[PDB]
Structure formats: structure tokens, C-alpha cells
Image (cartoon, rainbow, N blue to C red; front, side, top):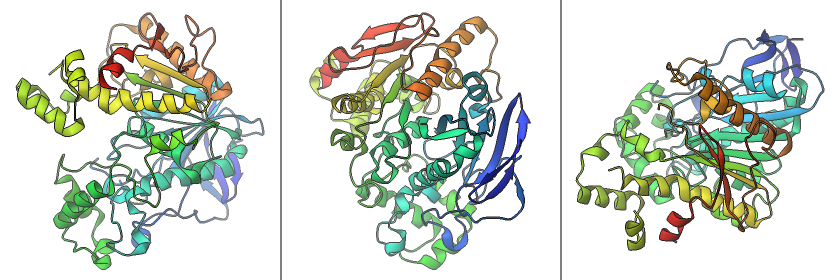
Length: 463
């Protein structure tokens, strides 16, 4: 029951908590040596039965190997029963993370929902998002979005092979948090991903998050190449520099470098949210939401926000997400960081929801208000029902409460993946679809409930 055949050969998984798991499946040829900075290519086939009982390495990151394009599968049974497939794209600011994190363990989903779960690795930071333009020749023109091409490659693997693991290739839901949700927002927009998935869920991110212009990305690349000792156009040193030195050079720039997808004219031909308005994802339902006041949580990793006086503060916010109309200021560190929450998280969520609703697609919107300890999205352990995992801020107190919110969110996400509607008796009241008409949202808290257009006042202050 543990051995499954795929287009590339047989894989041996294991039984775990009454479900089956396959770990470290290669979904692409390792992007090492002469394949460094090139789009992912199909994996080599093998003879015999390949072990899939250990995770593969994670991709290069501060935390690893350039050989890290692996995915993992949890399933109640490798049979032909066409279960919904949940395809998870982790977050980590396009800098760190992995699908093998215990936080994303798919056991609970698979057990409680009778679904297949897939988690993936994709290239990050300087290996996945180094925008080179034409500076190293046409072969590297896609380099600024390789981590997105990796995700598409994994999704193609799943569409081609998941039936063998008990999944329905025509019922895939892609979902992600933070940079993972930005990834889902990009994929929703992408012609070459259309038809690979049926539904999408975006947790505390959207296609706008961490998105770069070519001008912005090239300037960052120039600084990284300087630190790496690589002259523009020297392909020899681009491919021979040790992966750890290249990673060090980038990280040596701190915050004057952020990674993410680039509207480069080659993989991303236009803004991923604006594309939705032209019907890029017309038949695709989405479930989307945000963590209440999420930018206040960023002071933990960046306390400098708290040091600044009101004036310095506002000039900073203006430089990062401005201009800020006077009317917004009037509506409005705790008070002024609300501007960062709205511009980075809330606006892109509302623009995404408004675009899909205008296309007639179903949209379900939420706000997560539950206070729980710490891009600082907080839904994750409740959505995965992974309150018990390592790395999860599992602290004493609140246990029945935490279980109850997990039982609301976990089963809503499962219902959405199964049917395209999160509703059912696991919710204390119905969750109406978001329409231009009412702009309903579900609020997850100690007492979950529906609010009509909760973001409206703020949004009107701006728009």
C-alpha cells in the first residue's frame, strides 16, 4: 500500500497516524551547476523503487542545498478515489522556509477531511528571485521569478501524478500564507498556470505583497553582485561561485534588499491583481483573509519602528507605502502602523476580492481576530489543526478556546477545498459570499461572527 507508481517510477512511503506519507519526492531536475538560475526542468526517471520516507534538503537559505526541489504528500490511501487535493505554498518572505516544516504537516488535514495534501519547496532569495534582466544574456531573462516557475513545475507534477496517491487532479486547491499567499496571487494571474488548479485560498497576503518592479529589482541585483564579487555579464563566476558565498553576499545587505516576484515582461507580464480584472481567473473561487492589525506584529522583528517620533514615523511610512492622502491621516507607532497594515495587507485583499467578484466568481472573505502569540500571519496552526507541533507557539492556557477556533477554520478550509463553499455546522453562523452588494466577511475569534463591509470606512478614507 506504500508503493505508488508515477510517470517517473515507483516511490515507497510510510504509514503514519493511520494515513500514508511520501516525503522528498523530486519534482524537477536539481538546479545545480549549469542549471543554476535556469527554469526548472522535468525530473529524471528512475528504475526500481525509490525511497520517499525522509524529507529532501531545504533550498539555500540563512537557516540546506541548491538541490532542494522536493514535495511531500499525505493521503488516506493511494487508490483511485479522487479526493480533493490541498497544495500548500509556504511563506517566509521569499527568503526562508520549507514544505517540510512540522508546522505544515498534512496528517491532520488528510485524516479529518479525507483529502490529499501536498507541500512543496521552491527556490528563494538569491537563487529564486535574482533579477538579471538581459545582463547575462537571454538564457537568464526569467531569473527574477524562478521560485514562481518552481511552484508551477510542482503543480504540473501534481496534476500529472496525484491520481496515483488518491487525489483528484481536477480538484486542486492551492493555498498559502504571507509570501505563500503572494505566490498564490501570482499563480492566479499566470496564463501558464491556468487550468492547473480549481480554487485558491490566500491567508494574509495577495499578489501585491513583496512584488517588485524591474527597475527596483535590478538595483538590488547590482548591489548583490557587487557583494558577491561578480561583474555584470560574467557567467563563469555566476555559475562557479559557491552557493554559501552567494547567499552570504545578499544577506549582507540586510533590509535594503527584499525578494519577491518581478513584473519583468517574461514570466509576469503585468501586475497580478490588475490581471484579475481582465478575467485571468474568471472561473476560480477564492477564500481570502487577513490577520487583524498584522503590521503591529512586525515591531518584533523590527523594533526600530517603535523608536521613531511621530514625524520621523510618518515620513518613513510615506516613503515605504505613500503617498498618504490627508483624508486617510484624518481617519487614522500603534496608530500610524495601521497605515502599513492597510497598504501591505488589507488593500491588496480588497482589490483581489473586488476583481474576482466582478468576474462573478465566488469569494469568501475573513478577518482573524483571535489573540495568539507570534510576515506574522497568525491563522496557520488553526487552519492546519497543528496546535501540537514543534515550532508552534504552544503555551499553557486557552486550550478549549484554541481547539474550538481550530475546529472552525480547519473544517471550513476543508469544506472549501472539497466543494468551493466553507459553510457547514462547524461554523456558529453562515458565512455569506463576498459580493459588491454587501461586502460580508467572516470574523474568526473567541465568538466568530459575520460583519458587513468591516473595512469600508478605512477603504473610503483612502479611495
